[PDB]
Length: 120
Image 1 (cartoon, helix red, strand yellow):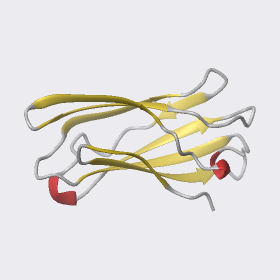
Image 2 (spheres, one colour):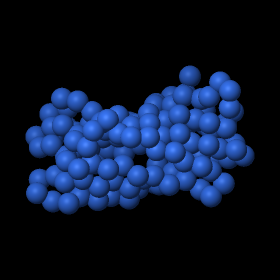
Image 3 (tube, helix red, strand yellow):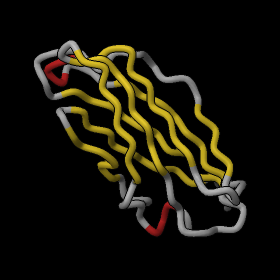
Image 4 (cartoon, one colour):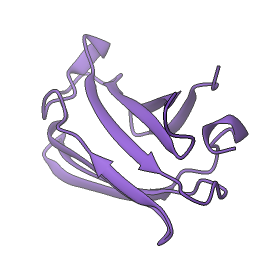
Protein backbone atom coordinates (compact mmCIF):
# COMPACT_ATOMS: atom_id res chain seq x y z
CA UNK A 1 0.00 0.00 0.00
CA UNK A 2 0.95 3.69 0.01
CA UNK A 3 3.16 4.50 3.02
CA UNK A 4 1.77 7.08 5.50
CA UNK A 5 3.88 10.13 6.45
CA UNK A 6 4.14 12.89 9.01
CA UNK A 7 3.60 15.90 6.77
CA UNK A 8 4.16 18.42 9.55
CA UNK A 9 5.31 18.34 13.16
CA UNK A 10 6.03 21.65 14.91
CA UNK A 11 5.04 23.47 18.10
CA UNK A 12 3.25 20.39 19.38
CA UNK A 13 0.94 20.12 16.35
CA UNK A 14 1.38 16.94 14.34
CA UNK A 15 -0.26 16.32 10.94
CA UNK A 16 -0.10 12.79 9.54
CA UNK A 17 -1.25 11.92 5.99
CA UNK A 18 -2.54 8.45 5.06
CA UNK A 19 -3.26 7.71 1.39
CA UNK A 20 -5.72 5.66 -0.69
CA UNK A 21 -5.65 5.36 -4.48
CA UNK A 22 -8.90 5.22 -6.44
CA UNK A 23 -9.64 1.81 -7.93
CA UNK A 24 -11.56 3.50 -10.72
CA UNK A 25 -9.41 6.54 -11.34
CA UNK A 26 -5.61 6.29 -11.65
CA UNK A 27 -5.53 10.03 -11.20
CA UNK A 28 -7.32 10.32 -7.81
CA UNK A 29 -5.56 9.91 -4.49
CA UNK A 30 -7.54 10.31 -1.28
CA UNK A 31 -5.56 11.78 1.60
CA UNK A 32 -6.83 11.52 5.15
CA UNK A 33 -5.17 13.96 7.48
CA UNK A 34 -5.03 13.49 11.22
CA UNK A 35 -4.09 16.48 13.37
CA UNK A 36 -3.00 15.88 16.93
CA UNK A 37 -1.76 18.05 19.76
CA UNK A 38 0.89 16.86 22.20
CA UNK A 39 0.79 20.05 24.32
CA UNK A 40 -1.06 20.87 27.53
CA UNK A 41 -3.38 23.41 25.85
CA UNK A 42 -6.07 22.98 23.16
CA UNK A 43 -5.48 24.39 19.70
CA UNK A 44 -8.73 26.08 18.75
CA UNK A 45 -10.33 27.47 15.58
CA UNK A 46 -8.04 25.14 13.69
CA UNK A 47 -8.07 25.47 9.92
CA UNK A 48 -6.10 23.41 7.42
CA UNK A 49 -5.77 24.72 3.86
CA UNK A 50 -3.75 23.41 0.95
CA UNK A 51 -2.71 24.24 -2.59
CA UNK A 52 -1.41 22.08 -5.42
CA UNK A 53 0.22 22.89 -8.78
CA UNK A 54 -1.93 24.24 -11.61
CA UNK A 55 -2.24 20.95 -13.50
CA UNK A 56 -3.73 19.36 -10.37
CA UNK A 57 -7.16 19.72 -8.78
CA UNK A 58 -7.78 19.72 -5.02
CA UNK A 59 -10.97 19.06 -3.05
CA UNK A 60 -11.12 19.59 0.72
CA UNK A 61 -13.95 17.95 2.64
CA UNK A 62 -15.15 19.18 6.05
CA UNK A 63 -12.91 18.57 9.05
CA UNK A 64 -14.33 16.58 11.96
CA UNK A 65 -13.89 19.53 14.33
CA UNK A 66 -12.05 22.81 14.83
CA UNK A 67 -10.29 21.84 18.07
CA UNK A 68 -7.09 19.80 18.27
CA UNK A 69 -7.43 18.57 21.85
CA UNK A 70 -4.58 18.84 24.35
CA UNK A 71 -2.71 15.82 25.77
CA UNK A 72 -3.19 13.77 22.56
CA UNK A 73 -6.69 12.89 23.69
CA UNK A 74 -8.09 12.93 20.14
CA UNK A 75 -7.53 14.25 16.64
CA UNK A 76 -9.03 16.32 13.91
CA UNK A 77 -9.67 14.20 10.84
CA UNK A 78 -10.07 15.78 7.39
CA UNK A 79 -10.21 14.28 3.90
CA UNK A 80 -8.58 15.89 0.86
CA UNK A 81 -8.81 14.51 -2.62
CA UNK A 82 -6.10 15.15 -5.13
CA UNK A 83 -6.72 14.80 -8.84
CA UNK A 84 -3.46 14.29 -10.74
CA UNK A 85 -4.54 13.87 -14.39
CA UNK A 86 -0.97 13.86 -15.72
CA UNK A 87 0.46 11.61 -12.98
CA UNK A 88 3.12 14.24 -12.14
CA UNK A 89 5.30 14.53 -9.00
CA UNK A 90 2.85 15.33 -6.22
CA UNK A 91 3.58 18.68 -4.59
CA UNK A 92 1.58 20.55 -1.97
CA UNK A 93 1.83 23.63 0.22
CA UNK A 94 -0.21 23.75 3.38
CA UNK A 95 -1.38 26.67 5.50
CA UNK A 96 -2.29 26.15 9.13
CA UNK A 97 -4.04 28.64 11.37
CA UNK A 98 -5.27 28.16 14.91
CA UNK A 99 -5.26 29.76 18.35
CA UNK A 100 -2.91 28.40 21.00
CA UNK A 101 -1.42 29.71 24.25
CA UNK A 102 -3.12 33.03 23.75
CA UNK A 103 -1.65 33.58 20.26
CA UNK A 104 -2.98 33.47 16.73
CA UNK A 105 -0.70 30.86 15.20
CA UNK A 106 -0.03 30.55 11.44
CA UNK A 107 2.36 28.49 9.38
CA UNK A 108 2.89 27.93 5.68
CA UNK A 109 4.88 24.88 4.67
CA UNK A 110 5.68 22.69 1.72
CA UNK A 111 5.04 18.96 2.18
CA UNK A 112 8.47 17.57 1.24
CA UNK A 113 7.94 13.88 1.72
CA UNK A 114 5.22 12.44 -0.44
CA UNK A 115 6.01 8.82 -1.28
CA UNK A 116 6.19 7.81 -4.97
CA UNK A 117 3.14 5.55 -4.53
CA UNK A 118 0.99 8.61 -3.78
CA UNK A 119 1.19 9.78 -7.40
CA UNK A 120 2.91 7.20 -9.63
